[PDB]
Length: 215
Length: 80
Length: 80
Length: 226
Image (cartoon, rainbow over all chains, first blue to last red; front, side):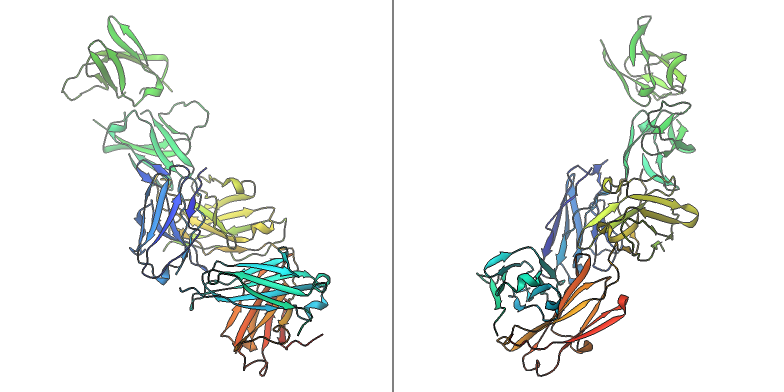
């Protein structure tokens, strides 16, 4: 066995800045003086591309902004001026077995607070016996965000589903939907519903809340 | 030795200074160890080329070359 | 290999697993290095036995065994 | 030229098997070794093994021993991966891949990749979505813009196509990736407009689900008290 340990799981990096992406082998992938490590782009919607073979050998038609170096266990991909074309995963694959590393993402802004909006279940959903309360948290940066749901003051963790858009191709922000699903019977036994968003742009979370029976 | 291929299979061009030493080369399926027991001389025009079979827990018989993980072709000269 | 003697002179009983490796054995006159380039096979009934001459700064000719400090006899089987 | 050419996408039921092909061209086929890398949704690459077309010898990843079988048809320059006792976790792309080079190397490089083959493993029968309009909290919100929502729940298979005002409202929209909820997909979308635009002008969510041949429109209507 060989256990391929890539490191950051995601990097965000400004254009013209220098990314560096690590890889840690568990077992020394070096044979006869060579090292058999393999750096690999992958755009969403495309196959993987070979970038760098044998730890340091830049493949045909790969731009010289990419550079690989390391030895034994410890290897590094370097991207020197990053350009927007770089934005992709990057995995590090040994060629002694075939094990892959848990691929670093690499994203191309100024912090931006989410715009938060809360939506009670629609009347149409409440015919169903299920009830979903939706919070949209839109156009924020950075991606790290945490949502806590409360019902009548009590945190609810079960039944929460979060979905994130990919980083927007124009404005570089993220958006998220957080949906609390409960039974209709439970929904109508409570009045206050709250989604709280913790994000680095505020010292305390943004709170959106409604009382079910108010207008 | 120079490691190349012959129809997808690994091929070893063995020179004179390797006579008597274990031949090791990495392969997807782990490390391969071929054993050369050959008239092995200097690399020249008079080459001979043949296959070193895979041998798992079997004693060798009527052969002077064999590997233990992946069958390999071998080539060496007989000059001196 | 088993180191013995043949009329006061050192004698090497070389087995199959030594094909391709430098043969070293200590002697009053320092360390002796014989080079075996032989049909070297498995030790059996079909043995052959002959001498590996001492060779000081001379290229080898018409031989497949030689030592560089003290002439040595060698024996090995040809079986496979 | 060097190409690899996979099967098409395939839509299996749990417990069944699937058997994806790989068609090489532009090289000798019998001179390289042919990888089979999965990628699941939001997951890394995950090697399945890499059969030699010269001798037929093959080396699996431990986690896919038993569950995969790699084969080669030399006289069709085609590799084949069989995958058995399929489960929801099996749902992924699979990717056949040329090892370059030839030292006897551990090169392990993946110099040419196929297009990938999308496997989906589903027991959920074709189900049209429920489409719910999401108006703001009753009594409205403060501020110069307003956000509306549309919740699309309980459909199979993917995809749906969600639009706002038949595609004429495209700015200010966020449509989120679908997630599984007890074997059925759910997604939602938000649209943000200036408050002079709604509710004085209509905004409608449209959801097409090709597999069920359905197209549903839900106008967003302000909430009223109980």
